[PDB]
Image 1 (cartoon, one colour):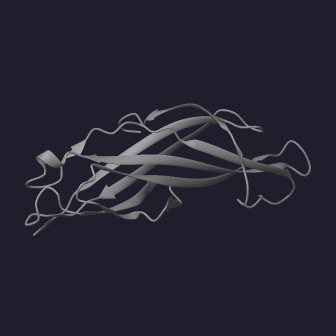
Image 2 (image 1 turned 45 degrees about the horizontal axis):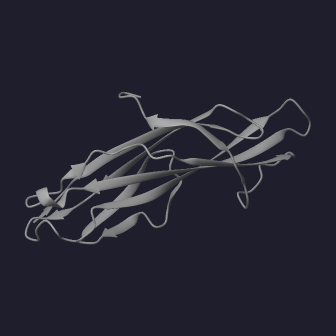
Image 3 (image 1 turned 180 degrees about the vertical axis):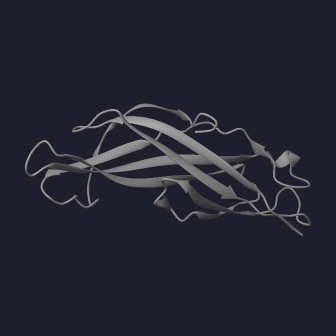
Amino acid sequence: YIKANDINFGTRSVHDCRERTGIQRDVKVRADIPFETDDGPNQVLRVTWSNALNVDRFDPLPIVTVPGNAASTTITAIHDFCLMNPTTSPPTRCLYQLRQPFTLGFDRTRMHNNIYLTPPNPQRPTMHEVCIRADECPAGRVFLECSTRTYGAIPRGE
């Protein structure tokens, strides 16, 4: 029969961009991983990634098939947000896009009865910024990449 499984991940990061520095973001995702108890440790797995916090879309499609011989699968969570500096007229309006990878690791040697995961590690994200002096937020058609100051796990309870 099909066992249900879910797991959550979260990564916090801080980025410095051309117009604004110290931008902190938390990104949280959930993975759901059914397991057919009749099909053994090398079965193909159908993973569904979903938003828990700040994910606008996944790249590529978040419905992923994990081959029977694969020990991992990776996805990129995409988060878009706008910031404004209203010290001038027109203001400086900036669109930001945070691209945050997550990887789900398996130990198929221990998967006779259900899934078995390996501990995750925070993965380095990238942030991208486009700014204009105008009354409208720019569209996300092109960006300049920011520098990543730090990244890591979200403290428990946060």
